[PDB]
Amino acid sequence: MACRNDIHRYDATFIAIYKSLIPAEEELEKQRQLMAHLENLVAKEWPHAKLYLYGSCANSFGFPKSDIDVCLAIEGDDINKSEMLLKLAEILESDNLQNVQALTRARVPIVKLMDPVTGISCAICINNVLAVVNTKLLRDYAQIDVRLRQLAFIVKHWAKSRRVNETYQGTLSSYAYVLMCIHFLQQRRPPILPCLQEMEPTYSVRVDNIRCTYFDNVDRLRNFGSNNRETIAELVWGFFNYWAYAHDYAYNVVSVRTGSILGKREKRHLICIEDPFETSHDLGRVVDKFSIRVLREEFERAARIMHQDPNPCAKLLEPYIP
Image (tube, rainbow, N blue to C red; front, top):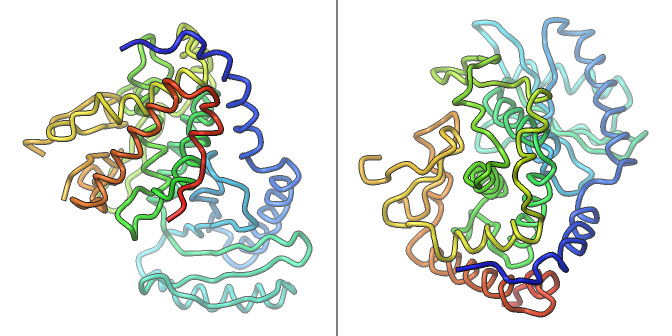
């Protein structure tokens, strides 16, 4: 079925929505100022350590928030994460940072602080390097074509407004939605995004028993999508059209790792979204036989709105009221 013939009248509204959703430059400047100070602070105690932002705050797909997540990466065979973080908390307190707290996430130790200069809060963990590498991959994809961050911010805001962005309710994580957006753009013809992991690699690190290898010199790919003329409203329409009507839920796996559709049957997997490095991890495994129906009804609602509604941008994002 074809796209509506007035689709481009809604391009500018989607761009306006996108621009309202991304972090303000003034907030990003504050985050970069705090990061430089924290990097210098940690280096005074552990000159061989490195600090990396990860998560929503650095993969180029995070909504505005006064919180950052940082991985302290350090090599060694006897890394005692608790002892390191206790020492770090003491150093942070000596530095006049505020509300320094020792926390845990599912037995993983975390130190949180509030910077009184910038007002930004920061949570630090030790050696969560796979999350850093996942973040790097997404940030690298985001450099290739502006339509990725535009689509992903719109999809993430749709999922928040429609209340289908909570894994505890059997719906999808923001990370899952970004992978879906990357794969949708890999699948366009002409393509908008390449498959970085299928290219001759320039980057390769091993995290535990996971090797992470791909072409990361993405500045050379800034014209990769230039043959594709699809605009943001066409891509929003096409994305929900794909998940509502075209995706084969019984048989297919979406794989950013290959840029392609893999088979499910030979390997809870009701909406199969392959993690690009931890390929045994299906990001949709949180979905169950009930929440898959809610997800697909919302996909269908979105596709019908994009296809027929006279104000699709506003109607698409109308909040779900329980």
